[PDB]
Amino acid sequence: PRRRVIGQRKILPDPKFGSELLAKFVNILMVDGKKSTAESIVYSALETLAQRSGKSELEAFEVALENVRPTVEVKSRRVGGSTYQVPVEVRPVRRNALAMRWIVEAARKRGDKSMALRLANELSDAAENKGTAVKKREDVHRMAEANKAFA
Amino acid sequence: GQKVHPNGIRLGIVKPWNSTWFANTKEFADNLDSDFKVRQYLTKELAKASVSRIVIERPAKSIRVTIHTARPGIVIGKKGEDVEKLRKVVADIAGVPAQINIAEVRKPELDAKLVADSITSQLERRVMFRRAMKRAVQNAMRLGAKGIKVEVSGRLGGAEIARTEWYREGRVPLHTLRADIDYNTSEAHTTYGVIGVKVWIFKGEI
Amino acid sequence: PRSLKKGPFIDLHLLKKVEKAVESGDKKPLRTWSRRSTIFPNMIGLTIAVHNGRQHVPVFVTDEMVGHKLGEFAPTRTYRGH
Amino acid sequence: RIRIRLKAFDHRLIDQATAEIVETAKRTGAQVRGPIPLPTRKERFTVLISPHVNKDARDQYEIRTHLRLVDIVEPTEKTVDALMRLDLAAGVDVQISL
Amino acid sequence: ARIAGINIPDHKHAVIALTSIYGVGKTRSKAILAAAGIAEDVKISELSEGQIDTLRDEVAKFVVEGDLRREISMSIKRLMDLGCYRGLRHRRGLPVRGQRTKTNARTRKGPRKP
Amino acid sequence: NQYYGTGRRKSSAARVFIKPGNGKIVINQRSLEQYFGRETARMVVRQPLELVDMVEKLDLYITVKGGGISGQAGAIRHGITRALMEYDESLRSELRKAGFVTRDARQVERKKVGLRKARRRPQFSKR
Amino acid sequence: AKQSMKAREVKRVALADKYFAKRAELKAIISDVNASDEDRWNAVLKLQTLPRDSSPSRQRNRCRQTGRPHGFLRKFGLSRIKVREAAMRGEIPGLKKASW
RNA sequence: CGGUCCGGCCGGGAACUCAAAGGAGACUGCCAGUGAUAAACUGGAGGAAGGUGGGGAUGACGUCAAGUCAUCAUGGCCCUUACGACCAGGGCUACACACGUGCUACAAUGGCGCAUACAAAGAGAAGCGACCUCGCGAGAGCAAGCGGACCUCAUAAAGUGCGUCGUAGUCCGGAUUGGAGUCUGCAACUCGACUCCAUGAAGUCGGAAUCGCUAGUAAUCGUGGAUCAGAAUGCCACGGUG
Ligand SMILES: [Mg+2]
């Protein structure tokens, strides 16, 4: 929008735990509209992580996210012919979302036999900082670092 | 060329329905066609006599047609035999026995269709088109029209290019849905071509 | 495709012609506009010039033809190459 | 006993006619269960506005088929007679199921 | 194991194993199973030879693999020298069933040439 | 005492009948785990109840018509909220804060003319 | 459409009016399972012989005012454009420039 | 509430969703700050509804000698035993290709099998067609009801509940090519679907490039309708997730 700045719609928390973040993650996972399948998958992923780690299902979710989220993000300015990809401070609201999206992408990329299992594995990787999403985050940070020069 | 036909947007608002009868899907289309035919016949017959529009109503399979005219002296005639004759043909066209009612329009220049017809006639007997239009508008204003827009299109004065020409006087609220916009079109069959005379007359705000 | 209960297509005129040919024993090319006709056991041996649009093309009736219509054998569309 | 159904294209007119019917019923006969409007049969008719070309342009029209039922489960000789001739429906198709 | 001409991968389920053989598919497989009295859940692994033999017999009862191909191929050949619409389509390499040859006839045609 | 609550979401119409004591959840002569499949939907239906301290304090006999699954659930929730309002009409402050009293203006936007969906234009070549 | 076109369909309509019961009976016996085979055959050839213009298949319904077969309507019996024209004039009862 | 086939089914009850008539109701009216003391603006309360509440119809002056003289009407020019008409077939569905626009795809959020849930909006008496019967089945017979909130077309499908298969060209996808049948109509051969059996092409997310959409929106799953003897992936619409 050129003109409109509006307060965003209310999203209801997760049925099992009571988390908006979880709901957001599920939404991100879901396309075509199939939420209940996606939600189920997410639950399954959580379960396996709990079975592996021996920790709380939400807390583990949180630290994985922490491990995959960046503080600085590049953005193109397009003033000249050469690329002016300036790094900008990312707000805590959308940072989470971006991380979730990255996780989803990584899961999609992965080749484990169950989709729930795939994302569980991704989460595990994030926890031990070795997966695909984390790698992506790392180079994003590196890219920002290189061009942190600009303001 | 772009806009809504005003008589069709106001048909359930300010304009009363020109067609006022119920028929089943089985018996709708044919009835409509019959009505159209009757309208055509009327047009053929009473073009020399000043007529505007007709309202058709058929209860208990016995039609009453309401005719909106300017002058009843030629439309009815001297006697009600001509009327009877006219009815017969309508009956023949439709199927069931026919009855009619006549309505004299008060202020003939307030109604658009009659004015349009007059303009067409003027065009036919070769008069200055622009001037005629101006005269018409003036007459309307004299009569107490709150607004009048007239519009003629194409082949004016035998020009090789089409001429779009229009006069606007008073207030003609084409967009106000509660406005009584009386809109009609008469298309002139001139020697040089076809000139389409469009006329809106704003009567009142209700 | 028709139901077998309904009964496959035969044109009357052509049938009559076929019958005549059988009785006659002349056979030869026989003119046919109506291409909808189903091939019959009596028709085997008869050559029939089927209308394809501009011209009649004679196609010889065989035993490998029973469950077919005449106009299929008529190349109603023509093509050579680009 | 007697189901009278009222069918018209205009709503106000139909309402008026219904009221008239009710009035007719009340004076001559007995009981009457008044007007019950049934769902409007909306005849969605989409017309291409342009004669040649232009797919995007469509005039969207609707026929409002208004239904009105007045229900009486009591026959009187006075009122049955003064209903077939005393109705004044004008532009409303009245179907009297006796 | 050889059931009607060609060999079958022993890993597969019953319904699917039968499908691999030309001439018989899913519904056919199901029918065969019904005839036998055995469900689809059992693989080629865990099966007695007697049981297999009945299945084989049933398959044979249906026109399968080579013979069916011959029947089809022979029919095609017959069509060819007849020279009907079906026949010329086959000869040309063009759609028979009633397709637009102008565009999207690419199954019978294959890949685009120029 | 008996209290009514009307519920609407998108295309759904829901009735909610509330009677104090015993604590029953009845949707079209069935239980919640019997009638509704998705857990999220169940949670949402329980949601208005959740905020307040009422578990076995009131019975709910409810009937729902139209809508979908999640939409239906939403409608049910709305009905429940309405019923609650009817019961007291003083504890509206919490409900408004939550965002439960408002029936969705978020509704079935009609498929448009010349356009492939409700807002979706047909995929077109610029030139 | 052309006047010729209109005339054609008029002729077809007339034929349909004439021939329908005769057509109908034949159709009925064709349908019938409890019927003689030779009789059925006879019926089918009758039908084949009996006019193509008499068939409701050849009945391409046209505009009852102008003659256009494309854009026909079973409610109004006219061309879409023509219907619209009528509608706007107020000449059709019920048909509103409406929204939903 | 009484009464019971545990069927709203009913003596009944008119309370309410509903239905559509008549309305109330949203106005910057209410509180504050800002602002020329004004318009107004940014908030706040109450309130079902918030600054145009959402969507639609609504297109001023006019542009492009824009489109259509094959809806219609038209000035004329011309053919007027022919550029006219009637019939029969072929075609308009051609096919080395080039493009546009829609659909199904490439998978385990899946494919299928077996249980089960939610509708909305329509359309109908040269019509729809419960019940019962036979058909794998499309459909037939048989025989009620409904000018139709009652009778029907039509079970909504995604979803949920189990089972599987274990990333293969697969139990993916269904193309094509053939076989066996059913309706429709004078008649499916060029030329309709559909019931079925088989068959298993390409394709494992698409180069350059490009496109739509700001919330019930996109994305996506179904359900109608209109033109239809007959025949939609189109189009108009209705709803589910979202
Ligand atoms: Mg291409």
Image (cartoon, coloured by chain):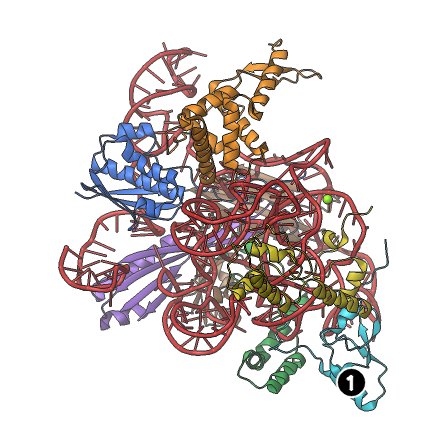
Chain colours: A orange, B brown, C cyan, D purple, E yellow, F blue, G green, H red
Residue B40: percent from left, percent from top: 57, 62
Residue at 66 percent across and 82 percent down: it is G45
Q: Nearer the viewer, residue E93 or B12?
A: E93
Question: In the rendered view of the protein, which quadrant contains the N terminus of chain E?
Answer: bottom right
The answer to whether residue A25 is seen in the rendering is yes
**Quadrant housing residue H35:** top left
Three-letter amino acid code of the residue under disc 1: Lys
- Residue B77 image position (x, y, % from top left): 50, 65
Which residue in the rendered view is the most extreme toward the front? E49
D20 lies above or below H188: above
Question: Does residue D32 appear to the left or right of F33 in the view shown?
Answer: left
Q: Residue furthest bottom?
A: C23
Which of the pair B151/H69 is nearer the observer?
H69
Residue in the image at 53% along x and 39% along y: F119
Residue of label 1:
C17
Ligand 1 falls in quadrant: top right
Residue occupying image coordinates x 84% and y 72%: C57
Q: Is residue H91 above or below residue F47?
A: below
Can residue G53 be spotted in the picture?
no
Query: Please, which chain is the residue tagged with disc 1 on?
Result: C
**Callout 1: few (<14), some (14-19), or many (20+) C-alpha neighbours within 10 Å?**
some
Question: Disc 1, ligand 1: is the CB inside 8 Å?
Answer: no
- In the image, residue G100 lies at what x, y percent? 46, 46
- Side (left or right) of C46 relative to B141: right
Q: Secondary structure at mark 1?
A: helix
Q: Position of residue D66 (x, y in %)?
A: 39, 56
Q: Nearer the viewer, residue A18 or E102?
A: A18
Residue at 81% over, 87% down? C21
Whether residue E53 is situated above or below residue H172 in the rendered picture: below
Q: Nearer the viewer, residue G81 or F125?
A: F125
The number of numbered badges drawn on the structure is 1
